[PDB]
Amino acid sequence: IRDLLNVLYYNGSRLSLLALGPVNAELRSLVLNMVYSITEGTTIILTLIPRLFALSAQDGYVNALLQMQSVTRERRLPLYEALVAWLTHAGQLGDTLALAPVVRVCTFDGAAVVRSGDMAPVIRYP
Amino acid sequence: MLADGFETDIAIPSGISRPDAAALQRCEGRVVFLPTIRRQLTLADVAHESFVSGGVSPDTLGLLLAYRRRFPAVITRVLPTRIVACPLDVGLTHAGTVNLRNTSPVDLCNGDPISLVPPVFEGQATDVRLDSLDLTLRFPVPLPSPLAREIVARLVARGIRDLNDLNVLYYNGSRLSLLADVQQLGPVNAELRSLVLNMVYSITEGTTIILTLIPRLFALSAQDGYVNALLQMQSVTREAAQLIHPEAPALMQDGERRLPLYEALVAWLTHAGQLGDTLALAPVVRVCTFDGAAVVRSGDMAPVIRYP
Amino acid sequence: MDPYCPFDALDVWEHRRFIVADSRNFITPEFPRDFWMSPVFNLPRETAA
Amino acid sequence: WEHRRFIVADSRNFITPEFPRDFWMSPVFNLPRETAA
Amino acid sequence: ARHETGGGVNFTLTQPRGNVDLGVGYTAVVATATVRNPVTDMGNLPQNF
Amino acid sequence: IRAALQGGPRISQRLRYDFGPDQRAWLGEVTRRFPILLENLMRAVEGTAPDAFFHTAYALAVLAHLGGRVVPLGDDLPARFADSDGHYVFDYYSTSGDTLRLNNRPIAVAMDEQSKCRFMEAPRRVCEQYLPGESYAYLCLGFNRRLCGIVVFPGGFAFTINIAAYLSLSDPVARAAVLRFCRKVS
Amino acid sequence: DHGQSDPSRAFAATANPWASQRFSYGDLLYNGAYHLNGASPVLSPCFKFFTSADIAAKHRCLERLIVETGSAVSTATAASDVQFKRPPGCRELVEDPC
Amino acid sequence: SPRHHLTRQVILTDLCQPNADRAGTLLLALRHPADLPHLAHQRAPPGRQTERLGEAWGQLMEATALRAGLVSFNFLVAACAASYDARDAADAVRAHVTANYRGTRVGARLDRFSECLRAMVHTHVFPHEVMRFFGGLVSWVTQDELASVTAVCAGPQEAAHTGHPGRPRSAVILPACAFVDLDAELGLGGPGAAFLYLVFTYRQRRDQELCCVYVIKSQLPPRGLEPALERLFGRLRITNTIHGTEDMTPPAPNRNPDFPLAGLAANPQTPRCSAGQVTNPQFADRLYRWQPDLRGRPTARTCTYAAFAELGMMPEDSPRCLHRTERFGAVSVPVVILEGVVWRPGEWRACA
Amino acid sequence: GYRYAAAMVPTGSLLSTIEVASHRRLFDFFSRVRSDANSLY
């Protein structure tokens, strides 16, 4: 998204992600779904409520958000033909980008920290 | 999962006619909502006799909002004295494989996460009504996942029209449609709030930058074929590019020490990417056929192994 | 004559044990406001002069 | 439990009273150094 | 004890034991005889704060 | 009081009191009721006898200030009145009806934008129960060792008043007033 | 106490005014109880000489003080590169005459 | 003889003590704390002090001397114990932490580790990202400053061999300041199995923050917990929205008017441009200009109140709760004893 | 509690069976076991 940060800290052990040539190009379809589904979402809700940005940032916007939280208070645009279609795509990326884990490591008779290249024991949720 | 599995008993009374008892052995695999994890329940808890709220009959949409407050279980076998089921949240069986049966007009391929949906389809709403005991067993319809994201998104969109077409589905090129009914104003406000809270939380200070990428996509869609087939033909932002050219805010408050785009994406995957689970229930179930075929037809059994 | 308030009002469920953020509420009586009269300070019949 | 409505005490809550034009020209806000009292 | 980790099954063996020192007074001697190689080089590493 | 309300102000609340939606109707009268109170402040403070004036919290805040310019008599001030600047000592005047004073002993409430209230350590008076601005029928009038004041209306709406820039007592008048109304600290 | 004399050399109150007395320049640098240098892993060898909280916690019976210095816990480590304060892991039975 | 999984880990005994807390307490692991002063430097909301956390966590490491360890549950409860409801029992959980753990001046840690949790939330590295579940004690071998911990990370608690053939099982032990049911407190009194939920509670104010840990037993699924956690803490979700956002600077007054897409789409006289004309100054600079401000908006990371996770279940017909007090040396504690618990953890889920 | 091996060989048996949980206050040690308690062994 910067093209149109690479410091990771785990275990107190510094990582790096930069090392870029094909990696920028290979990931390009991931970027173009992530941008669009957000920018479609932040305009339909901006169309349903045309006041989400024109309210004052700390007087009125907090007034409207608190009433949204409370349970007990009750040509043509292709507007409602988009809320269907936007939830098809945003409902899809929720599977492949949540990254549901399969494996838990419970160590036994060995090192607590598993190093790069070891053989680690594996359990699944029972 | 328990070490020997968990299997409930749904108690059958004594007075049931043989044209009613011999029609319950066609429930070898169905889906039954339990409210508890009791080992001995009654049929008067299972049927739609136990479903009805105070005075008010349910629609097809608010019927979802008492599914997630209940426990979906699968009948493994109807015995002549009782009905043995297995819940999906506690544990499946020893092997974890549970046999099912389709009610769907929709075929099942491998690896499809099964969600369950009420009988919304026309020409489909078939329930076994027991005349001997006034019992109405509404059995929900197992569907593949991306249809289940659609049909929930269809019916929520239908009620928003009625506060001030739509009913056309396609799967493998087969047209199929659903019933058009009036909707109760209660369970629509329970869904409209569940949308907007899970949606306004997806707006972050970092989203000011991504709004300024909208005029870049509309030009980029004219060069790559992947991107015009991405926007849509009936999209919205394509009409936003022909009217509004945004630009970014100039400076930031402490714009060195923080990552604005990274905050907007993590807060997007936890609210909007979670939304397909908020409206519907959890897709616990998917299909792992061992040796039978690749695709399970409608009306045939299918083995099931769990999933988050 | 209404006091300006940005916030309209909210709905707060409170279990009696889990009371946290101990603020205090404004007490108003049970009789209606037509009985709550305007203040009258009677001037004396004579003046200090 | 207990249920009630709830208005938040924010410091932006102000109040605007109205004064009469001849209010501050009152014989008590304007006292001499030596009165008859 | 039998417990399986890693496909293989560990057979951990334990044995509980006891130590009672029944000596009223001193009953054992260590005697430092010779000196092997010093670990620390006797050098000048000045200390920072 | 005139210096704090000369140009037309907005009296924001300085305290922390949550309302009710029916309770907007009560504060709506307090707006209409507002300038009549400020007169009958100055009337009822004038209306006291000069011998009986020196039981109020206002007189015991002046004598605690002229002493440092000793403890005032009767020991009405708290033991921690001279520690920080939030340790105020209040009065309680009736809002409706005849505007009177409703206190035996001056009442000390320590405080901390907004700030909460809190009593301190110490036959019975009903008006001793409630914090400043907590309820109807209580105007509150509290002062400092700095002799900066505050007038707290029902709901927590208040504004600070500097009395010390207007108290005009000369030094021989002051030390003749201190020695008569204080006591030397042991 | 510097109204009393040094038990080693009894004709002087100390041998350093800047190290022996309380709140001295020696105390302010090398006590555990003030924590100037507990953040760095490098050992200070006079940590056991100045920290008065450790000696006052020890007992006085010479029957047990002798055996406990037969198997005392060293403050240094040998697996460290330069010389480190010990990790809370390791224990080395190293005898202390000091 | 059912199936259960074990763990072993050589663990510093800085904060958890298997000498004091016997077999059957919860354990919570941590990430390695060298990343904490950088994550607070990175994920912090703007207009706050980022390096407050490293000073606060620093003073804890500067007070245990008078490596990713483990925090037992009784240590975490007693740290946050100054904000509970049954205050008499809350000063009984602290009353044996300072008097049974191997070490001196324990109160200098309890007024520091709770002070660390007062700095986790303002520096916005939330402790449920850092706190991870670890199993319950079935055996321990101890020494000075480290011990070998053997827990059960999966399975039933009531099956692992303790090592003593005198008492060759255990039972889950929890203090009575955190075991909050939602059966008797919601009216649902029917029989049935019940789950177990760990819950953190946040309260974001200007240097006035809290922490409350509970082991909540309920019959709701994780899919149906989000109303019930709002049910108790309705004021907390309010005060996190209204008092959480501070020193974020707003652009005032309203720089942004209404959003004119719906007003310009229905008119034919409105100027437009195609794909080849956009990103050019001779076509796009006659269109509408739109400069939205998002500063001081109470974002979802600034509006959190709770964070749950699964802990396990109780598969009986009815849960068997007990209420006893057992002896930790010379101080006895209000303890809720849970019987027959099967361990299954889950992911953390923010309730923003 | 009490010695479970001692009650394995009893010195004399009771005759009338009564709900003992009503007469709790007479006893120094009292414990109800549902079917099998873990702490019996």
Image (tube, coloured by chain):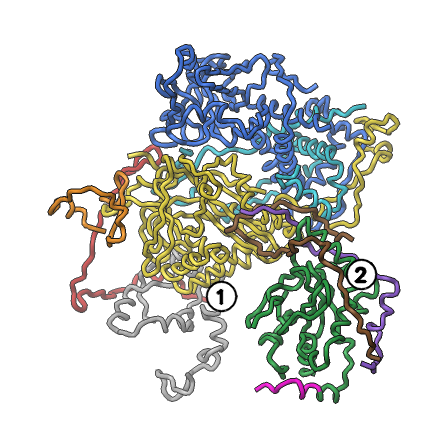
Chain colours: A cyan, B blue, C brown, D purple, E red, F green, H yellow, I orange
Q: Is residue B60 left or right of residue H1?
A: right
Tag 2: amino acid = Pro
Give coordinates of residue G26: x percent, y percent: 47, 75
The span shown in magenta is F177-186
Query: For the point 62% across and 31% down, which residue is it?
Result: B186
- According to the image, label 1 marks what residue? G37
Q: Is residue B44 left or right of residue G10?
A: right
Q: Chain of mark 2?
A: F
* Quadrant of the image occupied by residue I8: top left
Pointer 1: residues within 10 angstroms few (<14), some, or many (20+)? some
Between F52 and F88, the one nearer to me in the picture: F52
Q: Is residue H154 visible?
A: no
Q: Are marks 2 and 1 on the same chain?
A: no
Q: Classify B203 as above or below H101.
A: above
Give coordinates of residue F111: x percent, y percent: 63, 66
Pointer 2: residues within 10 angstroms few (<14), some, or many (20+)? few
Mark 2 vs mark 1, foreground winner is 2
Magenta span contains residue I9: no
Q: Classify H127 as above or below B227.
A: below
Give coordinates of residue B208: x percent, y percent: 72, 40
Query: For the point 58% across and 30% down, which residue is it?
Result: B279
Give coordinates of residue H103: x percent, y percent: 38, 62
Q: Chain of mark 1?
A: G
Q: Is residue H20 left or right of residue F92?
A: left
Query: For the point 48% across and 69% down, which residue is it?
Result: G34
**Looking at the figure, which quarter contains the N terminus of chain B?**
top left
Query: For the point 45% across and 50% down, which residue is it?
Result: H178
- According to the image, label 2 marks what residue? F9
Name the secondary structure under disc 1: loop
Name the secondary structure under disc 2: loop
Tag 1: amino acid = Asn
Q: Is residue I31 visible?
A: yes
